[PDB]
Amino acid sequence: SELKQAFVFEFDENLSSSSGSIHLEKVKQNSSPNYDYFKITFIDGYLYIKNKSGVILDKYDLKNVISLVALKRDYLSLSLSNNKQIKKFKNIKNKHLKNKFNLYVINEDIEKRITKNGILEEVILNKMLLSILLGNEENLLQIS
């Protein structure tokens, strides 16, 4: 009875952080035949914006935010996760991984639930999306 294709994410950085749960779905499209598109719907979670003092300045509810991302279909060549444990989408703080498959964000917030607050929020959501996905692309392999 669990939610299907739904996973926990954790994002930690100096000036922002986030955690919660996301639903991933493959998105049919013809604009970029060498890419797979994924829709990310936030089920639960908060986006935190912090000052340099580590003080939380703002807290944003991510619930029902819809994000759209894409990466090159070469990721399909990755070996499967070995059913090792439960798949999750976490970064490692200050570790900026190489972007092997040209993962990029098409739209970080389709209804501008958060990004209507300003440019800063846009940039932060974009960086968060890349951070929880890079290094974790094999998690996308049996996502339909």
Image: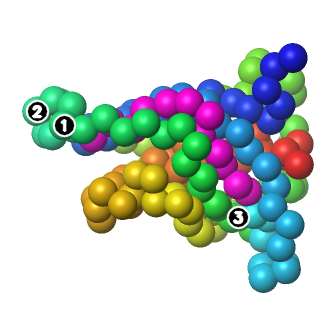
Residue indicated by mark 2 = 53
* Closer-to-camera residue (138/107): 107
CA neighbours of label 2 inside 10 A, class few (<14), some (14 to 19), many (20+): few
CA neighbours of label 1 inside 10 A, class few (<14), some (14 to 19), many (20+): few
* Residue found at the very far bottom of the displayed protein: 31
Distance from label 1 to label 2 (Cα)?
10 Å
Q: What is the three-letter code of the residue carrying label 1?
A: Leu
Residue 68, disc = none
Residue drawn at point x = 16 percent, y = 30 percent = 55
Residue indicated by mark 1 = 57
CA neighbours of label 3 inside 10 A, class few (<14), some (14 to 19), many (20+): many
Quadrant (top left, top right, bottom left, bottom right) of the N terminus = top right
Residue 99 seen in the figure: no
Distance from label 3 to label 2 (Cα)?
35 Å
Extent of the magenta region: 38-49
Residue drawn at point x = 56 percent, y = 30 percent = 44
Q: Position of residue 84 (x, y in %)?
A: 80, 20
